[PDB]
Image (cartoon, coloured by chain):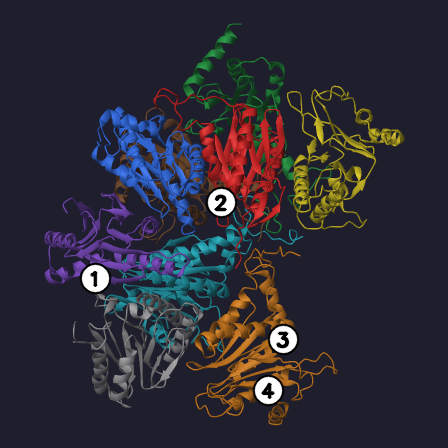
Amino acid sequence: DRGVSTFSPEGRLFQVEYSLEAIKLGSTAIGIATKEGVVLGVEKRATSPLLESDSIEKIVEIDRHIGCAMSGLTADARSMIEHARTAAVTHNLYYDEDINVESLTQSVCDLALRFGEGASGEERLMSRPFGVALLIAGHDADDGYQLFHAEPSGTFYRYNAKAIGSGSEGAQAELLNEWHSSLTLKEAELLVLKILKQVMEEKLDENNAQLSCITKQDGFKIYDNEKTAELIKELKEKEAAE
Amino acid sequence: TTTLAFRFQGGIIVAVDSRATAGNWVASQTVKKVIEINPFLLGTMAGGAADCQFWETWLGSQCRLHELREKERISVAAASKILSNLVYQYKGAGLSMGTMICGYTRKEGPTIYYVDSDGTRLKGDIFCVGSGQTFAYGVLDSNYKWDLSVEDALYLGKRSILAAAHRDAYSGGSVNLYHVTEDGWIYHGNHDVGELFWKVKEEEGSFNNVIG
Amino acid sequence: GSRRYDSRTTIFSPEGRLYQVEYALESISHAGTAIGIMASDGIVLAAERKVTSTLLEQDTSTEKLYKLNDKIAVAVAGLTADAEILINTARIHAQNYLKTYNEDIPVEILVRRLSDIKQGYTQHGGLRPFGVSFIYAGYDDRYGYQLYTSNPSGNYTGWKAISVGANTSAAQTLLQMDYKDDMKVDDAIELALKTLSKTTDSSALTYDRLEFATIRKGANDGEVYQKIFKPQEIKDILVKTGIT
Amino acid sequence: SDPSSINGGIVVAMTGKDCVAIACDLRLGSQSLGVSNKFEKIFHYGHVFLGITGLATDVTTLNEMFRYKTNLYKLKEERAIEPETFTQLVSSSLYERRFGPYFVGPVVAGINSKSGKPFIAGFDLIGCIDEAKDFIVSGTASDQLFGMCESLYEPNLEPEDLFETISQALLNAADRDALSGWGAVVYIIKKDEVVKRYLKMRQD
Amino acid sequence: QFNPYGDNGGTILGIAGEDFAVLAGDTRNITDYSINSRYEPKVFDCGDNIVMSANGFAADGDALVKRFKNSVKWYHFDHNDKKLSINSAARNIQHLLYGKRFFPYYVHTIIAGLDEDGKGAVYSFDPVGSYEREQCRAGGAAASLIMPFLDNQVNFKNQYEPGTNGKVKKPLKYLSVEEVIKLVRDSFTSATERHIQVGDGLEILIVTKDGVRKEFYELKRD
Amino acid sequence: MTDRYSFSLTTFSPSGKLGQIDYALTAVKQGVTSLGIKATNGVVIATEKKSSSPLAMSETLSKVSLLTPDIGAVYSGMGPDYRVLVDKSRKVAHTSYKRIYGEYPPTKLLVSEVAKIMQEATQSGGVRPFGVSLLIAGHDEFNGFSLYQVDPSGSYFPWKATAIGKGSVAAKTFLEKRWNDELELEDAIHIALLTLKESVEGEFNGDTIELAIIGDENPDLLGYTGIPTDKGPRFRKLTSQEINDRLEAL
Amino acid sequence: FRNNYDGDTVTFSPTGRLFQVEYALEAIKQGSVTVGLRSNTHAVLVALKRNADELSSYQKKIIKCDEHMGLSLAGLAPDARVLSNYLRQQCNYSSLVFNRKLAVERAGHLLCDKAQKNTQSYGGRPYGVGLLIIGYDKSGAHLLEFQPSGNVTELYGTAIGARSQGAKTYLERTLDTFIKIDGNPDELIKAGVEAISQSLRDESLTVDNLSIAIVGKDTPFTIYDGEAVAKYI
Amino acid sequence: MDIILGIRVQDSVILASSKAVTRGISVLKDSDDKTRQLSPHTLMSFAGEAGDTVQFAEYIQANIQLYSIREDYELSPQAVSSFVRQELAKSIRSRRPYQVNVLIGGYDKKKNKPELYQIDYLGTKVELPYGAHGYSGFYTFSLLDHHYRPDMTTEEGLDLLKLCVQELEKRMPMDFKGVIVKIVDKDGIRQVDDF
Amino acid sequence: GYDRALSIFSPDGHIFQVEYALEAVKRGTCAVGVKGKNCVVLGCERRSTLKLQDTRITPSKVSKIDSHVVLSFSGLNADSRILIEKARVEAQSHRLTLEDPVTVEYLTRYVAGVQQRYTQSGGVRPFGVSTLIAGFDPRDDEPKLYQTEPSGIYSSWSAQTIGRNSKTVREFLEKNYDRKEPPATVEECVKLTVRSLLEVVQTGAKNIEITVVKPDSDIVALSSEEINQYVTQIEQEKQE
């Protein structure tokens, strides 16, 4: 039986390659980055009517200036998000300044490869890599708003807008046409809610969809359900204006 | 070094002096002895300056880590007992700790905890730490009321440091005031103790030993 | 490397079962039969040996009855080799509790402790599970007499009368028709022998192939005396109750 | 100063014609203050009796440690511990705590049921086995007991008369010492029964 | 019986201007009553418009500076050459000083540069760990000779405007970089006469927004 | 360099029975015959020498060994596996019982320490079971003489007389009929030889039949006089001359 | 199509080869092209970066190791992120202890022996990255090629990655012109851009797709990017 | 130093403690409470070295509470005191020795008995009809020897404890500032506000 | 050490040791949770096939973690005790260092985090247990009811069921539980949870256990008589 380190005849680690398909099975995360802020949109995807849909969490604060979205097997991300708060917090303790986004992302990517069978004293703290991919959003004074996609591949790209999850293929087709550098914060919110509706498998309502932004002034804020209801009513209007 | 904190109707007044010495030589006369742990907790530095400087910036880390995991502000009760467990592990290795962790949540009311390197964690209503602590106590016990105006309580705090800074050697320098309300601490400015003395002597008539 | 030769004794099956723990249950169904009955005023432990030749000296032999302190005896069914290992870890944990609280160990603690040892090997380690099943008869003031069986899963539950070993099913159905709650220690003895007499592979039932030990409160001052019978008390009690 | 004299106590033990006696005081002091008069010093495993003197907390630590060995010894072998193997055992427990030992003076007394011989032995600190057949003493007032026994004792006393001899040895030594006093227990171990007597003495 | 702390005298001085800061220190390196070296710098450019001096025990001092320059390199390699600012470095050197606390460093440290706004900033450390931002701080052996003279010529302490009779404190100014150099040079000429461990030469490192300039002066050889 | 076998090589075959303890019990049935008989005043154990060649000396080989001065052992199965198990038998007897209680372990006691060594040769990882069965004859003060068999599984049993090895099926049938309750150590010696004469086809010299008693104590082998408390060793392996006496007594 | 000796690194094949080390060498032939060449006074790295798609940015390819040594990867990013971190530390371990700029040649061997000890032992993915390590010490300019087998060699010029062969051909002709260009850093960068244009499969050079780095007798290791490489296309 | 006083009567253990806590020159608090409720029927007063007391009293308490959830049962006071005596024995051999003294007052429900155990810092427990620690012990024992009857009702016992404190106030050279008095009977633990 | 990578991805993108773990929870006895206006009610299936088994001393399916947090479970009985030991531990640890009892959501996050850990540690097989953690936060009367599973993900529910025949019970709870209006009182809620169970237990008054947990640390177990009464009423009510 294969080990966990084995390469294929192509030169790809089996587990790391297989892991990418676990992300395809996850729920939809959309991220649009503008010059005024980044908007994070998620399909909560309740599984019953008895399931209370408010306790489900897919957006989490890392620090007042970094927020995170998850797609895939999301209990693995419990371990990744804990590392991140420590790196971000420990780094504000040693140098009296908030991490960059670009540096924080890279620390979680180093962590990702750690699978193995053990040798000497060296920690290998998984048997298979983190079965989850993350959209790290955030803002520093140096490079404005940024948006990153950190995959268990161990590589991260900075994106203008990426969408991962079940509807990744059809979602990113719509972004490629709709995005340009001149979106504001209130147009991106309606643009995420329009794309979230095309790839969604339910009815769009306030209970099973969540929005989040990141501005310098106010930090990282998750919208309550009340505010999201107004933006859902405001989508139906612009499509009947036409 | 003379620092005091005392509960009252409107929250907590924290007043600290400023002078930091090494024997006869006065090292420096501007020492922010009050450490901003976070926007709702104040910690005072008394005794061994290093220990309290370092281990209460570390304490601000554990407050902001516990605020992200649970998503709620941290009790004053919990913040102090994170710190007594830290210095208890080190005990006898020779560190010196003497702090008041002061905060004001809705469920506890305004609270003070006084953490010591012995391992002591005391809840209290009036505290006073440092060499001049006995002088500050005298003025504070006679004029203290649970019901007191916010004007009169700022002015009572300022006078407790002045009474200590005059008699005791090491304290001196400058007074800082802080008013811990529900929204967090507001810094009430720095007062030089040399210019303050003639002001108090004038208004009240206090101080007659000194011809000045 | 090592992976080729690896049995993997801890994986799940395609249906959410543990093969290797199932099989431990199978090897316990070949070993000798053991029965325990709970009366109002004592407990009978009675076990049938797997050996029976006459060269063997079954008279001083004890491979079924063990005392864990002076209030808890167990019976064994499975690998007798394996069982001596868990009994010394129990003997030691029973005593640690007497050291630290100056009070005889509750039956509930000593049973729950052994179970988790067994659980331990199927959770991690890659070691083969234990091949043993215990009946614990013990006395404590909290519930009086208590009876507990544990198997190589680690799941234990109390009982009024239970049996592990060969034909567990057949022995349970004979007991079920006869057992009553008003039984005394005399009545229980007579039901225990008779039930082993109906299941034994050989038609003859002899005093030498039976092991037998009770726990009675007829020891003075509100106490309990465990006796593992001598071969001469068993012989007389087999003629008394009319099995031969 | 010495750990022994912080709490005090004294044990003595004799032999006679087919029996042993063993006695102690019940006082438990914290230097000048006397705290309690019910603190037993003699504990017994089966038919072996063990007196411990010295620092009161080591007494209680060694009393749960030997109850742990003789219980586990009794289950595995299926006979009670015998006095000869118990002496070896007391000595080996003390010795592995070689450095900074228990500050104690154990006395083993018990009739061997095998041979019928009465048997005593004493120890001290690290683990030196004092073998005698006359009498054995421990504790603060060990000098004073030695004086009493040596003039009083004589080989082979019947059980009723050995009770008179060891009472005077304990009772006159104790009254001439500061750190021993209140109450006294004499156990007459015969070969079948054990008689336990509390003695009336001076409560100053 | 090894006594692991030595002494090497020497004194250092830091003055915070409005757009410049100086850290100066004497170059004489002693042990007891022998002069070991005329010329031995203690003020180092660490890159990023930080200057740092640890004065006191020269062996623990040189080591603390080697490890700090090692922390500036590793700052660049991780956060993509974001320049460590004087504010940042301060909380960092606090972590190296405190990392030993049961065989501590036995040095008195001063760093100086421009902070975010662009005004001179000096930080002063204790050996045990804590640190405070000052306007002016001396250190080393003759620190108690130069401090009081500086409190009188910068902060105008205990000076009152003439003809007000102590009822109006003297008005304060800002200092020019040319003026501060003359203050430091006067201090250290005074220092030499009365204290036996200052001399041979004074070296001033001036930190402006354009870089770091060195200037070297002769003092008395005796 | 590393050991990365931590997993059991003994698993449960799907119909119970641990596969490796079954096999090892077959290598115990290939070994050379060995048997033991208990009397009321001793125990005898006897075995046959097997010779690699006529060149090989056989006196140098010990096939009966001493564990303590009162407990002797003899095996059937594999030679290499018994050598290492007799040395681990003496250490664990001295270290968890001689030093701690003084006297030498009782015979019940000692069998249990040896059975834990066997047992942990399947529970543990990386190993396979010892390919031997032991007979352990000995004498303790409070139960007299006794005789034990410790199998590669770990189970032990008291016997009155038993045999193991290739002639085990034939031997135990004969001992079933011949044994009695009244027996001398001298009479038993005559039964032990008579049986083991049927099982050995090779040369039956008294050089090549090693017999040893756990009889009674020898004042002569003690090595020192003047302590009436101490007693000699109860074990005594007989020389070749003495065994040639009992052969001509057939 | 998957062999029988593809399990751990311990296994040898009956041909004699080690298959798992050969599989890690395919991880280089799917990375993006990168070209290194040196004269006797300047080393130069010219790498063509790779975006993931349009909205995406570009993936870094050139790592500043120190101020006189830098390497460029082609293959798996996290494997290089361990090997570049290790050289950094070994360059500090020389400046601290011996106060010696770590000679380029010695840093190659140090890297090699770190790759070897993971193909000897059971478990341990072999490193699936090919580095080019340029640098300038006391013995002049140096350019190394490091295979994942571990074998390091000294060259006047090489390339690795997808369709590298078209560039490596241009370097075999012009080797005799660009080797003599000394004391002129501009022309040596020009010869390196032309090399990598031969390997393109019509991706087209761009100001955001190209990355150059030089190091010399007088310059520190510096990376040009974005607007800074507009002059050199 | 401190004063901790324990008197056992017909059906109650009464424990008293000192309200004061003095660290150095100053008295810092006059309402502090030096006693933790281990269980619904077990109270434990403690006193001794600075800072160490508080850590060692919360420790014991967590282990006793854990046992109560784990078996769903209340440990008798006999069993609780042997556990506390075990933990002090460990520490005195270990690197850092505790100096704590404790009185454990409890009402065993199995026996319908009050019981009082005194454990000093060496690790020596003894069951008593009344105990104390420190220099405060010296002054009390000689009143109790004289007035105490074993058949006293709860209300007389409190009248005997008013007398013990009045003798302390007159002779000790350290202020302690009255006492908190607590009763443990079969109904639970109630604090009588009067001294 | 023993550190084989027992749990690995398959090419379909599911871990096969985790799917196998969740099938094991299906064969388990059935446990139901429903939260009323201001109570929770945990109903559990007792295997009553067994006869001559004493109920006085036999471990129940509801094990109190603290004095206001209860936990129920489906799956392997043996492995379940391992979670409950680490949970009782975690509840006293959190009381020690921060003060204040654990809030139900935190006690779940710990327990759910243990089941997640054992899906990465090499050498360990996943847990075969899914729990319902229920109770009241301290100084509050909002009922809370959570479910963990051997994937490690946890969610709050208004009603839920785990174990065998769960689809049939869940269907009944989607019709008979109005999300807006809970069972009016504590007595109506018990009558909703019993009536759900009697579909898949096919009656037996002894088979059903009901534990009710109320605000302010009031845990009570309904006795056999009470259960019988309720069953007879519902049977008679429904019968009528």
**Residue that carries the numbered disc 4 in the rendered image:** F193
Measured in 3D between alpha carbons, the distance from the residue under mark 3 to the one under mark 1, in whole angstroms, is 72 Å
| The chain in brown | I
- Dot label at residue I127: 2
Q: Color used for chain H?
A: purple
Q: Color used for chain B?
A: blue
Q: Which amino acid type is marked by label 3?
A: Lys
| The chain in cyan | C
Measured in 3D between alpha carbons, the distance from the residue under mark 3 to the one under mark 4, in whole angstroms, is 17 Å
Q: Visible in this render: residue A99?
A: no
Q: Color used for chain E?
A: red
Callout 4 and callout 1 share a chain: no
| The chain in green | A
Q: Is residue H91 left or right of residue E112?
A: left
First-in-chain label (3 vs 4): 3
Q: Color used for chain F?
A: orange
**Mark 4 or 2: the one toward you:** 2
Give the vertical position of E142 relative to G216 (above or below): below
